[PDB]
Amino acid sequence: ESKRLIDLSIQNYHTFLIYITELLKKLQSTTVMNPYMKLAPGELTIIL
Amino acid sequence: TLASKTKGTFAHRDFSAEYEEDGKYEGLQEWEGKAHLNIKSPAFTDLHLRYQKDKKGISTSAASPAVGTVGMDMDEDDDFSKWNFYYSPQSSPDKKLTIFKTELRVRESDEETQIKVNWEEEAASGLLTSLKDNVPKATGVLYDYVNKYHWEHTGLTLREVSSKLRRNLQNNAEWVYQGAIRQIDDIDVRFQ
Image (cartoon, rainbow over all chains, first blue to last red):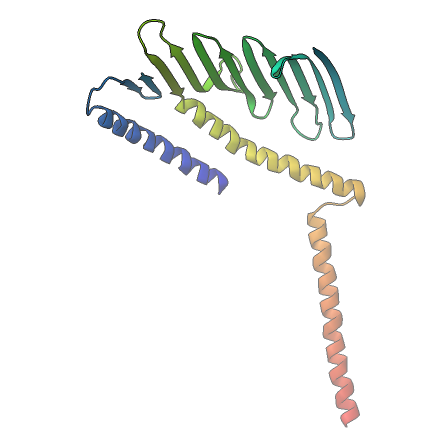
């Protein structure tokens, strides 16, 4: 049962991560102010 | 200035602990040196942790055959700061799956600052698989360990303990049953 739970957790994590990356990119594709950002599937860079 | 050299060694029947630390200390937080601990458990998987602190780097890595090698390296500099957290799987010790990475960069021109944070899904899922596969390994080694101690003390297993408890409970229950039957017979006889 522990391994089944861990399998479900890995599945849900990897299914969630693409969704949240898409959501982050959609939110950041809103406005362009003085600060700037960059998003990658596994990376986030912010410039002050 | 302090110069510290310590060695602590413990010896017993299912492992041995050997921790050697050397270093120097100045100021209030000016410590620099190394610290190597080695645990050798015959009953379990061994482990070796190495800590290193110098003025331009703090690297700490723990190597265990069961999990792999978990390390973190911190490099501070006036123009860049680099933090790396990696888990090298035991299957492929050559590669270092960077669990997380942090870059702080200052700009000598204008007024800007770059922060870069990187995470690996592959490293996380691989560590998750390693842990879920070490769970049965830990269960088996602990069960064998407790059985070994049971043999050391009595000379017996655990399932035999279950069977012994069952047979003793059955003997007591049958004693109670026969006591009840003979009591019914006795009370009937004395009533007659």
